[PDB]
Each structure stands twice: as C-alpha cells, then as structure tokens.
Image (cartoon, coloured by chain):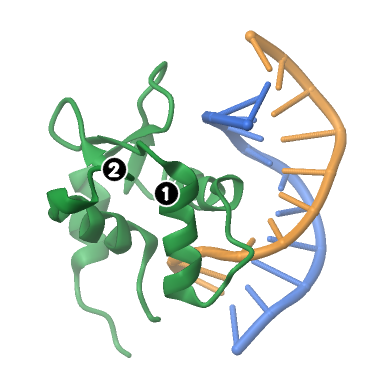
Chain colours: A green, B blue, C orange
DNA sequence: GACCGGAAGTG
DNA sequence: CACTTCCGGTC
C-alpha cells in the first residue's frame, strides 16, 4: 500500500534471497525477472489486487519509459534497466 | 507469448 | 497522477 512499482522492484532486488524471482544481471541498472509470474503475483499481493499478471505489470513498466525511470533491455527476455535520471526525480519528496 | 503503445477507467 | 485493465498490432 502507497508503494510505487519502481520501489517494489528495488525492494526485491536489494535482497539476493529473491533471486529465484528477480535479480540484477548486467550493466549498472540491468535486472531480469527469473520468474515474472511470481514477481507479478507479489505485486498484486502488496497492492491488494489479486488479478495482477505480467502483462499488466509490464504495461506499468512501459509507462516508465517516457518518465526516464527505466527502459527495455532489447533482446533479453524479461530484462529491463533502471535509469538514474528518472529515479533521482522519483526519489524526491512530495506533499502527502 | 513476448513486447509495444493507444485508449479508457480508478481513487 | 501512477497505475490497472484491456486489447489489436507485430515480431
């Protein structure tokens, strides 16, 4: 609850215990979803939204492209790359 | 079945 | 605004 998808993914990636569903892989920023159904299952669970799937989660990721929060790793399947430009901005404080 | 982005809905 | 839902492209 309250939590951004970009934050949720950093959360999982920060602990190598979650390697079986998501893990850093490649250049600075690059990660891949080893089990995207499980990643999406947890994201629905977190948001109380049990019809969540990879196809919906990924549309969320795709919206991050214009926001410069992340970008697709072309050719690698389930792999994306966080972009510091937009994360820095997203990390800044906001009213509540 | 990715992956894409348009379009419409949500609180 | 930051997603969720849905769906018709294209590979």
Q: Nearer the viewer, residue A89 or A12?
A: A12
Disc 2: host chain: A
Left/right of residue B1 with respect to residue B3 in the rendered view: right
Label 2–label 1 contact, CB within 8 A: no
Distance from disc 2 to disc 1, alpha carbons, whole Å, reads: 24 Å
Q: Which residue position is annotated with label 2?
A: A20
Q: Nearer the viewer, residue A20 or C5?
A: A20
Q: Which image quarter holds the N terminus of chain A?
A: bottom left
Q: Is residue A89 above or below residue A56?
A: below
Q: Which numbered mark, 2 or 1, is in the foreground of this view? A: 2
Disc 1 secondary structure class: loop
Q: Is residue A82 above or below residue A40?
A: above
User: Badge 1: how crowded within 10 Å, few (<14), some, or many (20+)?
Assistant: many
Residue at point 42%, 16% (across, down): A75
Q: Measured from the top left, where is residue B4 in percent x and y?
A: 57, 32
Q: Which image quarter holds the C terminus of chain A?
A: bottom left
Disc 2 secondary structure class: loop
- Image disc number at residue A43: none
Left/right of residue A63 with respect to residue A13 in the rendered view: right
Q: Which residue position is annotated with label 1?
A: A64
Residue at point 29%, 43% (across, down): A20
């Amino acid at each position: 609850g309250q939590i951004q998808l970009w934050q949720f993914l950093l959360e999982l990636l920060s602990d190598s215990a979650n390697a079986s569903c998501i893990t850093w892989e490649g250049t600075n920023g690059e990660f891949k979803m080893t089990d995207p159904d499980e990643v999406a299952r947890r994201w629905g669970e977190r948001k109380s939204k049990p019809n969540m799937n990879y196809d919906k989660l990924s549309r969320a990721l795709r919206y991050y492209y214009d926001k410069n929060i992340m970008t697709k790793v072309h050719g690698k399947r389930y792999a994306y790359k966080f972009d510091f430009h937009g994360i820095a901005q997203a990390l800044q404080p906001h009213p509540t």
